[PDB]
Image: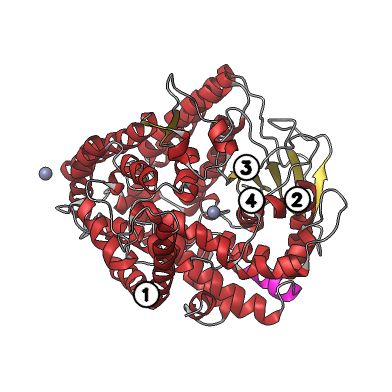
Amino acid sequence: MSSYTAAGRNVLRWDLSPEQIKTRTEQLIAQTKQVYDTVGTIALKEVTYENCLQVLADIEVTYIVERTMLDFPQHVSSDREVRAASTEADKKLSRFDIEMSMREDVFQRIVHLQETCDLEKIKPEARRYLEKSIKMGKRNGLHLSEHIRNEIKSMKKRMSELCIDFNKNLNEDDTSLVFSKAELGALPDDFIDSLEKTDEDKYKVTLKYPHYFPVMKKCCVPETRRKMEMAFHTRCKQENTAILQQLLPLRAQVAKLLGYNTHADFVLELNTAKSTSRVAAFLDDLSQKLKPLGEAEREFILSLKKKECEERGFEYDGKINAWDLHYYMTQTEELKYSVDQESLKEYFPIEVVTEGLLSIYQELLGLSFEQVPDAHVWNKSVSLYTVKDKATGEVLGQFYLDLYPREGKYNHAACFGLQPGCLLPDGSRMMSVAALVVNFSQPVAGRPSLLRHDEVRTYFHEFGHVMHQICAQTDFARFSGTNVETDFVEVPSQMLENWVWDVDSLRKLSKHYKDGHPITDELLEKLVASRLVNTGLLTLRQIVLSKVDQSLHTNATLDAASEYAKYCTEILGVAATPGTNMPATFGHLAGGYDGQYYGYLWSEVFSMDMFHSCFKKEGIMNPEVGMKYRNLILKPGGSLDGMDMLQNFLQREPNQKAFLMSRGL
Ligand SMILES: [Zn+2]
Ligand SMILES: [Zn+2]
């Protein structure tokens, strides 16, 4: 199969039945184990590049591809049975993945290969493959005595149970509060109308996000915001505090047994940040540079509160409490740049946004997008596109667009890698495949689907991952697509969001759905000018969370709540409510990427450096810079370190000048 057609390069099945998913799962695991069994028994002196490295690499490709037909349906299939089977498949496959990574016999063979092998006779990416594989083995303790490995296991198995419990608690929580309409003042009728009513003249308000935020952002009754904030930040307090008290010390022990000083050092080693000290300095210096901006905003908010308390006689306490931050930050947006989102959206018909988004990217990256006519999909609402390189006709890959909310479908925005763009056994390249999964407002009444600006920003964000997935071309599957450092994966996505704050780009993405008139120059200037409203406190709040995250993985004997309170008053200027335990509701800690929360802010600094220093310098639609970004930042996927690719693109080490200049510092 050629690199100049898509024909036959994508045969992923999206209509598998629950029994077919079960069968394929059982067959994948067994057949794949046999390959590791075969590599794990090769005589150490007989280990070679073809019978070892090439064997492990070939199996990684075939395995990852079969695995996606099995673990993806749980996120998009409309059939409840199919979804459950996929979830089950993902559980068996995930346990199998752990098993294989714990194969001491296989580790031995790769360690010996790297020795007896002349690393200078093989491609740089294959050297990286070996080094990274051996490194992952050491990180799993495969070089340690059997006694120590067993200890690490009994601890990791207990840390998984703890994280699953921490999360289960928060998810199964159904705490509720009852308020009279008087107590929910200022809240929209659309909000109140959707609330359940009790046998009293009261409305039920849960603690789930859809209820919590509009109440913290719009409720003009201070005491209501107060009770919500108290109840919301006390969820699972006992249970999860108890879990954290066991979990963090466990993370410390495991790190020690592995040879690291702290769990943080363990996590950060695989990131571009590299170490605990580097992250601490990153966050510490940022909050210092941001301090003055936080003092002004905090001051501005204070003048708004004191003033409003007099115009309603609520009483003033001279301070910004936790249950006041969102509220006054919203008031700020309405006074600085009154941007009516429900009005603006009318200028963003999904049809127009989609066409615009794709047009921009085709021109910027030298690509051509063509929709697949009668494409095999998991839902009639999904469209499939084939991606060719404008110049050569080369088919880089395909991407699916799943844009509307649907029962059973993943409810958050994301980009899934379905097929890696790596080499196949005969040297031919596997076509990359990605699925963009978002949930944009569907067409209501006679009006088409209309996107708010933040949704247009999400569309671009996710499409940034799609392009990373599709343009990434490596020799090995493990370095393909978005397999870059965790604190680097959000670089491609956040850099592309800059385009939705670009006047000229916005013109290409909007047209009033009715008469089709463009957005007024006056409104455009206002929209882009409001990009940084409240950036001070917002960023400081992100730094607070980032510090808590590092702290809980640098220590152990630490009280999560007090640590959070400490940074809240020291960095944010808004005290943490006495009696609450935000960290115990911090889903990021347990499951996920603990010790890496700073990653998002870390990535913004870099994306901002590239956008300003390169695209702004040369013109953000300049094809030359566009191609360099694709070739130097996207194309290599994870086959090169993040900082090296940044250097390659910038032609100097990255720095935060741009990130600070934008913020206005
Ligand atoms: Zn021991
Ligand atoms: Zn992202």
Tell me the number on the disc at residue 616: none
Give above or below for 368 relative to 407.
below
Q: CA distance from mark 3 to mark 2?
A: 22 Å
Q: Residue 243: horizontal and vertical position, in percent?
A: 23, 39
Q: Label 1: few (<14), some or many (≥20) within 10 Å? A: some
Q: Label 3: few (<14), some or many (≥20) within 10 Å? A: many
Colour scheme of the picture: secondary structure
In front of the other: 58 or 171: 171
Q: In this rendering, which labeled residue sits more in front, label 1 or label 4?
A: 1
Query: Which tag, 1 or 4, sits closer to the chain's start?
Result: 1
Circle 2 sits on which residue?
346
Is residue 307 left or right of 626 when viewed as pictured? Answer: left
Q: Residue 452: horizontal and vertical position, in percent?
A: 66, 51
Tell me the number on the disc at residue 291: 1
Q: CA distance from mark 1 to mark 3?
A: 37 Å
Q: Which residues are magenta?
A: 622-631
Query: Which tag, 3 or 4, sits closer to the chain's start?
Result: 3
Q: CA distance from mark 3 to mark 4?
A: 12 Å
Image region (quadrant) for ligand 2? bottom right
Labels 1 and 2 touching (C-beta < 8 A): no
Q: Quadrant of the N terminus?
A: top right
Circle 4 sits on which residue?
455
For image coordinates 51% across by 65% down, the residue present is 640
